[PDB]
Image (tube, rainbow over all chains, first blue to last red; front, side, top):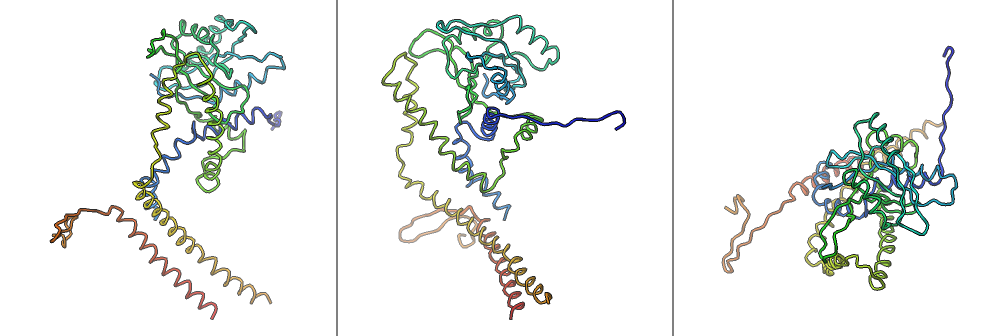
Length: 57
Length: 286
Length: 55
């Protein structure tokens, strides 16, 4: 602390960056057509998930 | 050649910077930048990039302006500081594909290796994936049309390496992770219908219009295979799938049993404490 | 040998129809039944505790 100190830090965001980055991140957590990998797990419920349900039991 | 590519949000945020430093011009046409990545590995990986001035003409569409010196300087310094990344291709922010783009890409087709083209939107009103990776190759046409540059769609994914995830998550503090549960899943199960709705509505209308009302033989032949895919499901009566529905509903019954039993187990402590704690508190109250 | 259950099958006399079938989800109904039976003891014991704390 002797002969030394610091300064506060804040950010700034507008609507463009907000909407763009939010949509891009949501899409990053989503699929291209979004209907692709859903039905996959839906049909994997009778194969994969079942074993996980057995282990859960 | 390349099955899939990896596009980091940093370049699109650099496009956000392109929409930032504009400073109210009154022109705001398409801007061609230079994308950088690693062409060594089979899968393409985007790290960072820079920006080069690009201008066109109002009337004549054949006008395109690039810079060799600025490109060699920027890529030179970038290669000087980081040797783990080289040139790959370019991208534009234009929503529409211009005919001059083949001549624009021809330069990097000569000087550099084969370049990948990326098309995005100036206004992020598109719910779908903003980034479309288009490889530039020469394919033999079935109709017999002269050989020309053809853009083929390549699947892509939006992801980050290590720190970028942290930076995004910190700068947002809004979006949520996968978080397996009720709300996270049901939100998808709700909005996905709209995700297909707006897209299909935006597509099949212009499709239906341009098919009958239009010209410039873009090789409709693939659309017969489209309609064929639409005909791959000739209204199945589910009669064969009845057993599958029975198994699925049986699994549903399993879920019912599990839920009821587990909740019955949880109810123990509650329906004990609600009595034993209240009666003791009441008797020791006075 | 069918009574010994070394394989899956059943005989016939008049018709002479041979039918072969199997039941893969063995571990499901067993663990489910075990869960039910075990939880029954929990609920019953709970009823005993409540009957003890009340009457």
